[PDB]
Image (tube, coloured by chain):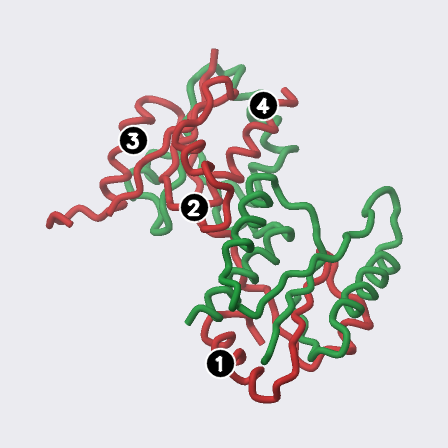
Chain colours: A green, B red
Amino acid sequence: MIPGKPWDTPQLAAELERWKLDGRDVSLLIGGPEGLSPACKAAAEQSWSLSALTLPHPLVRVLVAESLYRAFSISMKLQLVAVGTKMPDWVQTGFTEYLRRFPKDMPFELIEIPAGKRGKNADIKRILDKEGEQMLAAAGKNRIVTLD
Amino acid sequence: KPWDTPQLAAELERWKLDGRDVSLLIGGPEGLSPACKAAAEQSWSLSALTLPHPLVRVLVAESLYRAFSITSMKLQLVAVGTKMPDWVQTGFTEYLRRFPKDMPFELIEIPAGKKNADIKRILDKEGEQMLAAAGKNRIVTLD
């Protein structure tokens, strides 16, 4: 039972090197939502913990938008105002089309705010302040609800 | 305060009653600015949001591809093919079921089990197919 995140590049890249040199073939098993069968877990040479694989921040606004779509699915308008951290292409293309498929009578809109540069010794506090200025501008006089 | 379906469902009807339009604000990874937090009439926590299970095998495949990229052993990713969310790119399900052979590892998708009466659980049947695929390989599990 390996602690932490053994799939993370500093650990996995070194472990793959060892697996290649060992020469034996490797199977990495992932079950469904109910998990792996006891026989699979008993056969394992290494056991990694699924719970440590957390939700990437760019998907937060995706899950929230879906939550609101579902809630509207079962005059006031709602805006999701979110910082647009870059998500993977295999999500972004699908998410743009997902939003386009919403019914026209759904009073929901996603507004994405440009994410500030987070590079070499960037001042996070001022980056956050500038994102917040743009978020509050988009919200105008609406009721403000924060999710964090 | 926790973001979830029952609390969101109740709050949405409440929001209509005072009539004002509503903006839900999500910051960057480091959080919201002080001015955003000060302006909030209501605050929700996203702590209990988790990665959708079908994306687990996708993120693991990404990790494997990237680790191979910076380094006669064959590695197989043997994963139950849980249905993709509605917002993943069209054709991605098919891509994961027909993973390209020029990738540095193989992706074997176990069909997500589902009428017939028996005493085998769905995960018992999946587990039989997984151990068949794995054979005499070294086994790593993620669960």
Q: Secondary structure at mark 4?
A: helix
**Distance between the Cα atoms at labels 2 and 1?**
28 Å
Label 4 vs 3, first from the N-terminus: 4
Q: Are marks 2 and 1 on the same chain?
A: yes
Q: Residue at x 61, y 74 (%)?
A: A77
Check disc 3 and report the residue beneath it.
B131
Q: Nearer the viewer, residue B13 or A5?
A: B13
- The residue wearing badge 1 is B10
* Camera sees residue B138: yes
Question: Residue B32: x, y in percent?
Answer: 75, 65
Residue drawn at point x = 58 percent, y = 67 percent? A108
Measure the C-alpha gap from mark 1 to mark 3: 46 Å
In-image side of A127 versus B105 (left or right):
right
- The mark nearer the N terminus, 4 or 1, is 1
> What is the x, y in percent for residue A32?
36, 46
Asked where in the image residue A137 lies, by quadrant, the reply is bottom right
Q: Disc 4 or disc 3, which is closer to the eye?
A: 4
Q: Amino acid at mark 2?
A: Met
Q: Alpha carbon of mark 4 to alpha carbon of mark 3: how far?
A: 24 Å
Question: Which chain contains the residue that carries disc 3?
Answer: B
Q: Which image quarter holds the C terminus of chain A?
A: bottom right
Instruction: Give the camera-side residue of A1 and B65.
Output: B65
Discs 4 and 3 lie in a common subunit: yes
Q: Position of residue B141 (x, y in %)?
A: 42, 37
Q: CA distance from mark 4 to mark 2?
A: 25 Å
